Image (tube, rainbow, N blue to C red; front, top):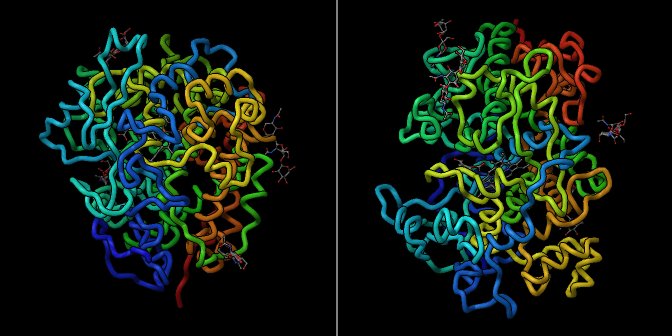
Length: 595
Ligand code: HEM
Ligand SMILES: *[C@@H]1O[C@H](CO)[C@@H](O[C@@H]2O[C@H](CO)[C@@H](O[C@H]3O[C@H](CO)[C@@H](O)[C@H](O)[C@@H]3O)[C@H](O)[C@H]2NC(C)=O)[C@H](O)[C@H]1NC(C)=O
Ligand SMILES: *[C@@H]1O[C@H](CO)[C@@H](O[C@@H]2O[C@H](CO)[C@@H](O[C@H]3O[C@H](CO)[C@@H](O)[C@H](O)[C@@H]3O)[C@H](O)[C@H]2NC(C)=O)[C@H](O)[C@H]1NC(C)=O
Ligand SMILES: *[C@@H]1O[C@H](CO)[C@@H](O[C@@H]2O[C@H](CO)[C@@H](O)[C@H](O)[C@H]2NC(C)=O)[C@H](O)[C@H]1NC(C)=O
Ligand SMILES: *[C@@H]1O[C@H](CO)[C@@H](O[C@@H]2O[C@H](CO)[C@@H](O)[C@H](O)[C@H]2NC(C)=O)[C@H](O)[C@H]1NC(C)=O
Ligand SMILES: CC(=O)Oc1ccccc1C(=O)O
Ligand SMILES: [Ca+2]
């Protein structure tokens, strides 16, 4: 007895059916089931949700009710006893650049977003939750354990709001609570253009027929464009330096200004759209604005898919790559392309790959300025350092020359994110991303670690000795048992991230399985996948294979020296070469005659 009635919170419309362009909402990708993969719908469930009361309450909500007979430990204690570390030396990945971490965040934001609950404009819940830590409704505070230094200095808890769910959002109940994915599931560049009709339109430059995206009008970066500023005050980007008063950037995705390197990436993409756009007009002068926009847009979608599948996943999945994502075989209308709820947690392996600093390099790739190396936390929601401190070129050089942080069992997440994370909404640099993650696993009703091992067909340890062998680490296995009492209670996020990495990969077996299946699906169930016969012509695909992130760089900055393989670790100047030597995307194949 199914239930697929429930729905409304969804912006729907009719389909075009022989239209060559994806919709903004993702609707109509699948002809037989039109809303599959669309934005503003529930995340798919690969396993049933697991709640304290079986429907909506998170585990750890009712301090008396246990999970399999035990109390589940506070997310912050786990963060404190297993995730933190003090010494940053020796923690960098010797063969993965800072761009490796950054692309991951970009693919992520393209695929999923479960925003927090509102009903809170002009709200005191907004305060009944930060001031007094009273648990209730959508307020599910992260309590501080005894002996936490934040006690003495911050309060009794860290505010936290539950994720949105469907059918409504206010006081609801009935079936099992399913969170929302506010963006399209397909890998389609929805982060550049938006996932809603409204925002997509406001992002475009409609005062002219060139099919370009709107650009900042207050500042330019050496003639090159900037994303436009965001309308909405109170702005967090201006709260961090009330003298600079530079607002956040307005983009296709709302998290765009979370950190300066993510904003840099968004800018690089915006720029490529316009470039691609003025170039296409030049070869087909009669094309109107719509055609220029959709056509460029489609090129860029094919770009992100290529870099992701050809250059990125192979070094995340490693030797497991082929075990989950076999050679492409054509569109499969039976493959469900929805992003699963657990994937949004599996993809968070990236948080343990973020180093404590971001650097800026001048043109010889040497420290730019005196205070060239900044601590990560000073850059959450920091747009002023771009606009008033050198543009994006210095940051892009850092992306190519610095390394990512390597995941390590005794040194998982940097304190820059574990104690000094900045929320939009709040006023301090004192949040814990690691604790938020664990708290979100429960909010989302995730099955424990062992449920997912079974799912992936991997052993399921029940004993300390069992866990030691799987984690191949006596001590961590130990900390994990003292806190969880049973491996069946270990939250998927930490359980999955504590495993050793597979050969040539950056994630372990459980994650490789969870990541691998998800990507296989968004590829096989995407009617618009770039390799799908009829989407692009044979000659257009031969052109699209020469796309390189190195090139994306050369064409949209004033950097003339770039690595050939921008994801592996490269040393300047030996591994860098003149832009003049890098393959360019050939567009003549897009030229469409007449008569
Ligand atoms: C600061 C933050 C980052 C870097 C300086 C950062 C980075 C990443 C990378 C590199 C990811 C994948 C390779 C990745 C995935 C996901 N993130 Fe994270 N991220 C920073 C900050 C946050 C915050 C805060 C959240 C929200 C947590 C919450 O539950 O409230 C966050 C989320 C996610 C996320 C879930 C997305 C969703 O579907 O709602 C990832 C898959 N990041 N980040
Ligand atoms: C740093 O990471 C690099 C990537 O993980 C790695 O180099 C890669 O090694 C693989 C080994 O299989 C090779 O991969 C390519 O080999 C042929 C081309 O000769 C292709 O047809 C294959 O499909 C495959 O893509 C490459 O030599 C290289 N891959 C790339 C994309 O550059 C380095 O070995 C790592 N450094 C160290 C010290 O381990
Ligand atoms: C808030 O943003 C301010 C910039 O908008 C920033 O101050 C700026 O940064 C430095 C001061 O530390 C100045 O630049 C340096 O270079 C000039 C070159 O002309 C030299 O004369 C000085 O050595 C100078 O330090 C900027 O001019 C300065 N701008 C202003 C208006 O002060 C603040 O530091 C930011 N505040 C925080 C807390 O981040
Ligand atoms: C929309 O596009 C138009 C045309 O490309 C932009 O107008 C040009 O802006 C630059 C700098 O202002 C200059 O070349 C001219 O002032 C404009 N040229 C023309 C032909 O109008 C305009 O800036 C864009 N609008 C937005 C909001 O980005
Ligand atoms: C298209 O995708 C479907 C769904 O993933 C594949 O279906 C599996 O195929 C086997 C053999 O027919 C079935 O017995 C299983 O029930 C299916 N497994 C699952 C988990 O659904 C199918 O193989 C794909 N077909 C092509 C031609 O690519
Ligand atoms: C999802 C992500 O990367 O988002 C954020 C994290 C901390 C604070 C703000 C945001 C945001 O999107 O506004
Ligand atoms: Ca998308």
